[PDB]
Length: 215
Length: 215
Ligand SMILES: N#Cc1cc(=O)[nH]c(=O)n1[C@@H]1O[C@H](COP(=O)(O)O)[C@@H](O)[C@H]1O
Ligand SMILES: N#Cc1cc(=O)[nH]c(=O)n1[C@@H]1O[C@H](COP(=O)(O)O)[C@@H](O)[C@H]1O
Image (cartoon, rainbow over all chains, first blue to last red; front, side, top):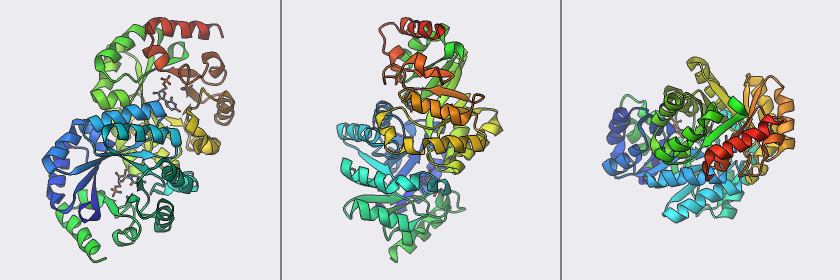
């Protein structure tokens, strides 16, 4: 992705979301849109963004249901024009396979969320995350998400998925993660609040890119 | 809930969803609406249903993000008129507490999904589910979801949460669960396809209720 930086656009107002995304568009190639924006403004916002900004859109829907419901969520999400969807691994292989089947049908991609970035991830997800990643490899998953806030776990995840797999990583900035350290292991970093809550989101994005280029 | 039966309305067309819900409204008082319907027809469908049918609405959004994102999802979902939201416990206590805080602010309820009903739940979720349920109890959660497809696990869940907690259970019918056995432990059953894919959804609901009344 352009500059190895993905904008997490979690503003909950179409006007603010459009303003900030337009201000930082020169510095990115992909926008992650999640439920805060979609549930506030509708699924139509995905195709609006994709057209207006000519960016790729990852739907961060943390898909975490039974196989049959997962298939329906993926179908609706790709129909809305998303390029990829983020799916939890913790509910197991059949739930992940359902999403992979729809992505295959529709010519799109699945990202598998292994370990989450927030403190509570330590309770249950962290102890299963290596096995969730290995499950991903066995299912043929090629795109993964893992935590900026724990670079030793990001390293272990990269070890499991290999160098050919694509790995993106949230928790940079607001949650405490560092762009340069995270990019030792991940291919791209996700950044939300550090950019979209900044007084000057373009300046915040540019500052991040400047530290990335230096690596 | 009326007749201990909650309709899982996962049709993805407003006209079909309205038809079936109207046909079975005499047999229920609560409708579970999830992402298949919401992502196809918009969040406004929640208030439409609540008004048209005068039913309680549980938003089954399997909420499974970091605390800050969970808060935004819950806020948008209650603003849309939902009475309650279903939240995963696997991501940990901070993520669950975020949802509880918004529910407290807005006068609504959180249901904690412990163990899921599909086969893949056995991989990772089942081994954590007793601890997820105990975490719920410690956080003061009073409403829980657990699997019709494993009544021995539903029994263990009920043991952890006590008799005062409210427990609803999906996986009845299509996934293999039985209404009567599940209601030995759960307060209410969730039923989707066995009703909404039936040639006569009212007859399917009535058939289920006749077997419930007999218990
Ligand atoms: N993908 C994802 C997800 C999984 C995870 O483990 N940690 C995250 O922060 N996220 C999402 O990434 C973004 C992080 O944004 P921020 O830079 O912390 O403001 C949010 O959309 C959050 O919901
Ligand atoms: N709530 C929930 C959820 C958690 C779980 O462990 N198992 C489920 O089936 N569900 C949901 O309950 C409904 C079950 O519907 P059905 O009766 O199997 O057609 C679906 O909306 C499914 O997504």
